[PDB]
Structure formats: C-alpha cells, structure tokens
Image (tube, rainbow over all chains, first blue to last red; front, side, top):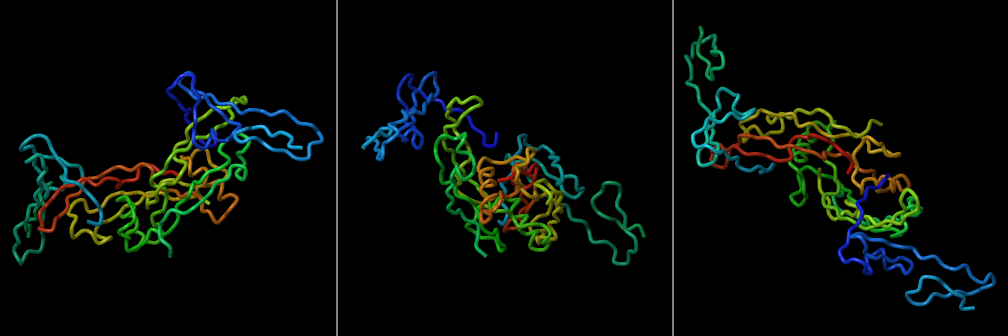
Length: 67
Length: 67
Length: 104
Length: 104
C-alpha cells in the first residue's frame, strides 16, 4: 500500500514511550509492551452546545469551555 | 583517474590467470604474483616491408607474412 | 544551468491525500534533489562510474541522457498510521528524507 | 511516454577517448536507464519511499520534478589499464554495468 513500513520495536516493557515528532502532540501517547509500541489517540467529550470560547490546559488534549 | 578502480588480487603463486574479456585476447596474458595479477602484452616483430599478405595461425597472436 | 544539489521541500500529508491513514505527523521536510550533472564533470559532485561513463557518452551522442541528480543518502522517519481495520500502529519508513544528492 | 526501464548501450572506449590508458577491453555493454516515472504510480516499477512521495507532490506542484529513472543495481568489471609509468595494471571498477533500473 503506497508507502512501505516496518513496525517499530522498543525495549522497556510497560513504560511510557516518547517518540520525537509523534508523541509530542498532546492527544497521542505510546507505551512499550511486547517489545513493540502501542499508541492511542485520545478522544474528547463533545461540549456544551452553547460554548463561545474554548481553551486547553498546557499539555492537555481536550479543550474545555473558558466560557 | 576519471573513473575509479582498485587493483585485483589472486590466490596462488604462479597461476596462469584466465580473466574474461581481458585474457581471451591471444596477445594478453596474466599470472599471479605477489597476490596480484600481473599482465603482459606481447609485441610482434615488424615484418618484411615487401609483404602483400599476412596471416595468423588459429588463435596465435602475431601475424606472419603469407606472401 | 544550475548544478545537482539538495533543495528544500516540506511535504504536507493533507495536501497529498494521506491525512486519512496517517494520524501523525501532519507532514515533514522531505527535501529533494535537482540540478544538472554536467560536462566537464564537477569535482565536488558524487557520481558512480557508470554516471561518469554516461556523461561522456552524452557529450557526443545526445540521444543518451546525462546522468540524473537523485537522492544518494536518505534517512527514515516514524509515522503513526491506521491499518486494515482502524488499529493505530507505529512504523518506521525507510528512505523518506533526502540527506544528500548525487549523479546516478 | 514510455516508462522507466533499462536500455542497451555499448560503450566503445576508443570513442570516449580512453583507449590511450585502457588496453583491454576495447569496450563493453554498459546499458542505461531511461523512461518516465509516472503517475498514477505503476505497480511494476521499483520506487524508493521518497520517490513515491515526490511523485505525488509533482502531481500537484509541477515545479517539483518527477522522480528520475536511474540504475538501481549495478555490477563491476575488470579492465587492464596503464599507469603514469606505462605499467600495466589490472583493476576492478565498481558500478559499471547496469543490471536494473528504478525510480529514485
């Protein structure tokens, strides 16, 4: 399929993994398990349907109503 | 040079080398010495200046006057 | 005119149509190679023997093209993509960033 | 346009001006690579990851060139040359014969 890849390995079982350029987006996190990298993309609550302003906490993924 | 090569090597001292596309010329021959294939190009004696027809024995290097 | 050389290029996956299977990164600096492989040869340019031979042939038979300026050292990047059925998986992609160019 | 493949080419050392330092062979079949690296991509051609990316970009920004068709597998030959002293040396030259082409 178009571009060709090899899935990444990693060494330390069960600990958080920081991949430059991937994992620095607040909504993406990885953890090394089974010698390979399992990552997740967190999902956010839909929010009060009358919010006019929205802010996200430093390092936070989901935005919330400022007001 | 303009194009880049490296000196070839061979194993056995005093072995007659058969090198494809070099050695198949009846006038060129190589032998192994100092782990290096040394080649020589045989030169042919000038022939009679009154000669009108030369000939080469099957697979010989130098032409001789046939008449 | 201008001689073989690396050049800037930022590649943006949305623009390329891939945003839908590549979740991250949103893009990257691929760079690229462009420029002539000239005659006279340019001492500073990396060329294979064959490229040199071909430059010479070109110089007298111009239906034979000059050597091409192409990537010559590349490096990998990581991407986070969606498999067959929505499983986020992390892979390393060889040969994605042009590190240096040469005549081939 | 015809697409990226290998083509026959016999190079005659006497013609490129080299017979004065190369004594054997008188020439050789070097072949060359020529043809378009197209879009849509063609399944049968071999392309580097970066080449595929660059093909897509080009399809949208025609000032970024297409990938270039070049030799991707080469093999060596033996030549009997002639040094600064007329000594007769037999050397191997890498990267002189095109075994296969690809988009890079």
